[PDB]
Image (spheres, helix red, strand yellow):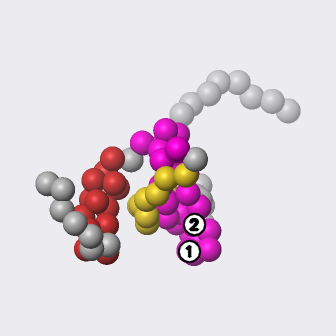
Amino acid sequence: GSHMGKKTKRTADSSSSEDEEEYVVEKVLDRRMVKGQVEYLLKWKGFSEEHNTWEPEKNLDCPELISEFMKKYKKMKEGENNK
Protein backbone atom coordinates (compact mmCIF):
# COMPACT_ATOMS: atom_id res chain seq x y z
CA GLY A 1 0.00 0.00 0.00
CA SER A 2 0.97 3.63 0.54
CA HIS A 3 0.68 6.57 2.94
CA MET A 4 0.50 10.37 2.97
CA GLY A 5 1.80 13.13 5.22
CA LYS A 6 5.23 13.61 6.76
CA LYS A 7 6.74 14.57 10.12
CA THR A 8 10.26 15.22 11.42
CA LYS A 9 10.95 12.98 14.41
CA ARG A 10 13.81 10.94 15.88
CA THR A 11 14.27 9.46 19.35
CA ALA A 12 16.47 6.46 18.59
CA ASP A 13 17.99 4.71 15.58
CA SER A 14 20.46 2.14 16.92
CA SER A 15 21.47 0.68 20.29
CA SER A 16 24.63 -1.38 19.81
CA SER A 17 26.09 0.98 17.21
CA GLU A 18 28.00 4.27 17.09
CA ASP A 19 27.10 7.47 15.24
CA GLU A 20 29.95 7.44 12.73
CA GLU A 21 33.71 6.99 12.37
CA GLU A 22 36.36 8.29 9.98
CA TYR A 23 40.02 9.31 9.67
CA VAL A 24 40.30 13.04 10.36
CA VAL A 25 43.29 15.27 11.11
CA GLU A 26 44.12 15.70 14.79
CA LYS A 27 47.15 17.98 15.01
CA VAL A 28 50.45 18.91 13.35
CA LEU A 29 53.30 16.43 13.74
CA ASP A 30 55.95 18.31 11.78
CA ARG A 31 56.62 21.10 9.27
CA ARG A 32 58.77 21.30 6.14
CA MET A 33 59.00 22.69 2.61
CA VAL A 34 59.34 21.00 -0.79
CA LYS A 35 59.43 22.29 -4.36
CA GLY A 36 58.99 25.85 -3.12
CA GLN A 37 55.79 24.64 -1.48
CA VAL A 38 55.15 24.71 2.27
CA GLU A 39 54.21 21.24 3.49
CA TYR A 40 52.78 20.25 6.87
CA LEU A 41 52.47 16.90 8.65
CA LEU A 42 48.91 16.16 9.77
CA LYS A 43 48.22 13.32 12.20
CA TRP A 44 45.30 11.37 10.74
CA LYS A 45 43.40 9.82 13.65
CA GLY A 46 42.58 6.12 13.41
CA PHE A 47 46.02 5.35 12.00
CA SER A 48 49.71 5.08 12.88
CA GLU A 49 52.79 7.10 11.93
CA GLU A 50 53.03 4.96 8.79
CA HIS A 51 49.98 6.84 7.51
CA ASN A 52 51.71 10.19 8.05
CA THR A 53 51.81 12.22 4.84
CA TRP A 54 52.71 15.85 4.15
CA GLU A 55 50.12 18.20 2.65
CA PRO A 56 50.07 21.72 1.17
CA GLU A 57 49.31 24.61 3.53
CA LYS A 58 47.47 26.43 0.74
CA ASN A 59 44.92 23.60 0.73
CA LEU A 60 44.44 23.50 4.50
CA ASP A 61 44.73 26.42 6.92
CA CYS A 62 45.48 25.43 10.51
CA PRO A 63 47.24 28.31 12.31
CA GLU A 64 46.15 26.77 15.61
CA LEU A 65 48.40 23.73 15.15
CA ILE A 66 51.37 25.68 13.80
CA SER A 67 51.11 28.46 16.38
CA GLU A 68 51.55 25.94 19.20
CA PHE A 69 53.79 23.53 17.30
CA MET A 70 56.15 26.48 16.85
CA LYS A 71 57.07 26.14 20.53
CA LYS A 72 57.68 22.41 20.03
CA TYR A 73 60.07 22.96 17.13
CA LYS A 74 62.25 25.04 19.45
CA LYS A 75 62.50 22.50 22.27
CA MET A 76 62.78 19.67 19.74
CA LYS A 77 65.33 21.42 17.51
CA GLU A 78 67.87 23.64 19.26
CA GLY A 79 69.60 26.14 17.00
CA GLU A 80 69.48 29.91 17.47
CA ASN A 81 67.18 32.78 18.41
CA ASN A 82 66.17 35.49 15.93
CA LYS A 83 63.79 37.39 18.20
**Is 41 in the magenta?**
yes
Q: Residues within 10 Å of mark 1 (few under 14, many from 20)?
A: few
Could you tell me which residue is drawn at 57 percent across and 75 percent down?
48
Using the image as rendered, state which of residue 77 and residue 10 is in the foreground: 77
Rendering coords of residue 67 (x, y %): 27, 53
- Rendered position, 3 above or below 15: above
Q: Residues within 10 Å of mark 2 (few under 14, many from 20)?
A: some
Could you tell me which residue is drawn at 57 percent across and 66 percent down?
52
Using the image as rendered, state which of residue 50 and residue 15 is in the foreground: 50
**Quarter of the view holding residue 69:** bottom left
Residue tagged 1: 49
The quadrant in which the N terminus is found is top right
**Is 66 in the magenta?**
no
Q: Secondary structure at mark 1?
A: helix
Three-letter amino acid code at the position of disc 1: Glu
The quadrant in which the C terminus is found is bottom left
Q: Secondary structure at mark 2?
A: loop
Rendering coords of residue 80 (x, y %): 22, 66
Q: Can the viewer see residue 21 in this picture?
A: no
Q: Can the viewer see residue 34 in this picture?
A: yes
- Rendered position, 16 above or below 62: below
Q: From the viewer's perspective, is 12 left or right of 83?
A: right
**Quarter of the view holding residue 19:** bottom right
Three-letter amino acid code at the position of disc 2: Asn
Residue tagged 2: 52
Could you tell me which residue is drawn at 52 percent across and 44 percent down?
37
Tell me whether circle 1 and circle 2 mark residues in contact (CB < 8 Å): yes
The segment highlighted magenta reads: 36-61
